[PDB]
Length: 182
Ligand SMILES: [Zn+2]
Image 1 (cartoon, rainbow, N blue to C red):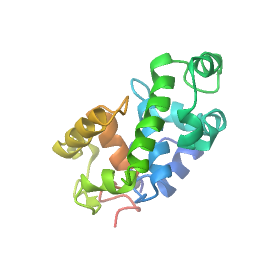
Image 2 (image 1 turned 90 degrees about the horizontal axis):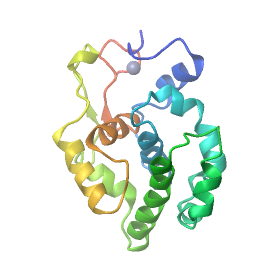
Image 3 (image 1 turned 180 degrees about the horizontal axis):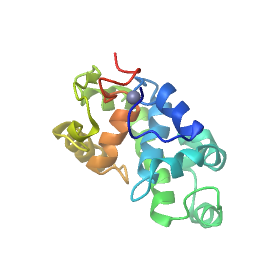
Image 4 (image 1 turned 90 degrees about the vertical axis):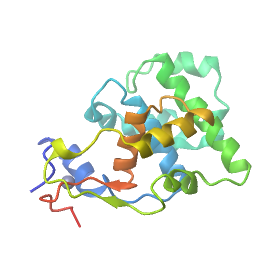
């Protein structure tokens, strides 16, 4: 059995089976996922997942240095790229997020340490047997959203942050029946 929210799409099955809820501790990889999670605001994950390679291609493999140097002209070219989400606020958010991440990392602050601090450094494993008993935001995601906003990140509302926590294994929200549950 798998989590009920997975579709029959093999791209999504692989994502569920191999990536979702798996603890991620690399700062750059965490950066990529907070960005991809913000791109999904108002949309479904499959839309963003199917576009992930396109994002990696026009955002310099989520290297924050190169992204941070992007300007209005880059935003305008990206707004013409049908392989990503053509939404000005969403494109600008990736650029703001790169700059925000750089300002932390250059000040000696690991982004990985930062996000992991909100779950006390340890994956929180669910006891829910059904998706209805799994929240979409928590006090911890509220705290992470407030901190990210204060530090200059964009498209990081509390629901986005909780999805990010799930995706990157800060919480493990596979249902207890799922073969991926501990
Ligand atoms: Zn699962």
